[PDB]
Amino acid sequence: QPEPDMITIFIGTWNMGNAPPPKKITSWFLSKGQGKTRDDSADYIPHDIYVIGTQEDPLSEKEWLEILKHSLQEITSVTFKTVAIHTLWNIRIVVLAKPEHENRISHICTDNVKTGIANTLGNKGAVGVSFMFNGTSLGFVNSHLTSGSEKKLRRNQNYMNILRFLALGDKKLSPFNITHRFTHLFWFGDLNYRVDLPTWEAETIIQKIKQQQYADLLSHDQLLTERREQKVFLHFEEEEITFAPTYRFERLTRDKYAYTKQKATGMKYNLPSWCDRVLWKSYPLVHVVCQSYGSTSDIMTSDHSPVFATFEAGVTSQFVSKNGPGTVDSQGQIEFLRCYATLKTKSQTKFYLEFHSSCLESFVKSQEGENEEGSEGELVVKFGETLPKLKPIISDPEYLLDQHILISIKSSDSDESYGEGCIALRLEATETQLPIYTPLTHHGELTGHFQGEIKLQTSQ
Ligand SMILES: N#Cc1ccc(N2CCNCC2)c(F)c1
Ligand SMILES: N#Cc1ccc(N2CCNCC2)c(F)c1
Image (cartoon, rainbow, N blue to C red):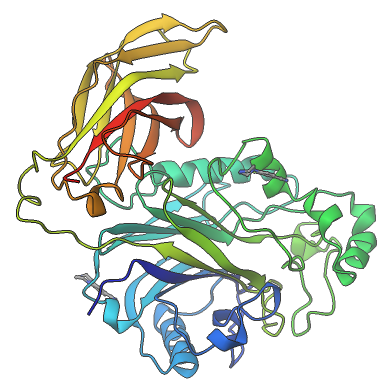
């Protein structure tokens, strides 16, 4: 039984509009409809992992699990194992995996975040799942963000609360939020960003959709434009959208968008919009390739169409040598030269670094850096040649070049992280000084940069 170096992952997001699904939803799991669709020749090939996010889901977990498993069994003739299911209000995440993966999957975590306060607390937020797949950490966030064309800022706030407070993955990674805890992080849901065009242009928008001419609409998609201005989802990717807006349809057809203001909408227009989205963030130089991104055309119980995305994702094996795990491997070391952090902070305190990696027995604290002023006002924290020599548990290059070092820069005064980032050990050379770089974030906002040189010694 060889361990895989690649898996495929299905991501689905559907706002079910508080209606039961139709009897057949197989088109969703087959990535068939509009957009970047999956080749017919793959229909019987199961994905390794299926992650299903619903919003406005009226079903019990039991009712939905039965529909999902029976759907996949009809497609694949495989009885999928339930990895996890977590529901907050009517927001749900289900993770299913091929039975051969049962022993490869461990450290399963679930959590939820409720967004807003009083008025704004009661139905929006996120659910999430994480786990290990052999040596690879996977996270999944299904969020239902604030609705309404005039609330993009609220949505961006919801995003930041979710990434700050969703507690998934390795708790030992205490300085790091979910945007740094996983080899691969998929974030999807009814993110509720709208096409921000005048109300009077509704029929023009519909015309453009019927012509499959999305360019003039996507140029006003609030998620793309907010991402472009680094207001939200910084360092996440999204595949090009080549499918029609997935909201707001008349139910039981896909022929009609229902956009006009109604008492039932709070007298808000719902111009056709790409509310339903899949984004990802993977550690640097890990294989991740989107192989489908689209919407179904034949599932019409909701005022949203289901969205699918599929990915090839690189994975690593659970490595054992004569030495680590359970000791260091003296044949391995990670050295840092000419390193400095550049920080946006207006504060003057001393800083130190923490290095966190599953290639280390535990995290490593550096000495304090030396603060200097940058030529354009910035705080520069010089580590020069002072950073420690890191001692990985395994020196085999087939292991070590697949690893990553998370970096937090912390205040000596408060022990609070001012910035977090990640460095790949997938180097062009070993025993060679090579440039390294990561942006630093805190609460998912850019706070600085870390750069320098690395010298990696493996047993080869
Ligand atoms: N596919 C799969 C799969 C793998 C592991 C678990 N479990 C749950 C919590 N207890 C121990 C581990 C599971 F439910 C499903
Ligand atoms: N409209 C738009 C838009 C275009 C580009 C980006 N970026 C740059 C490339 N890398 C990250 C994504 C973006 F966020 C939004």
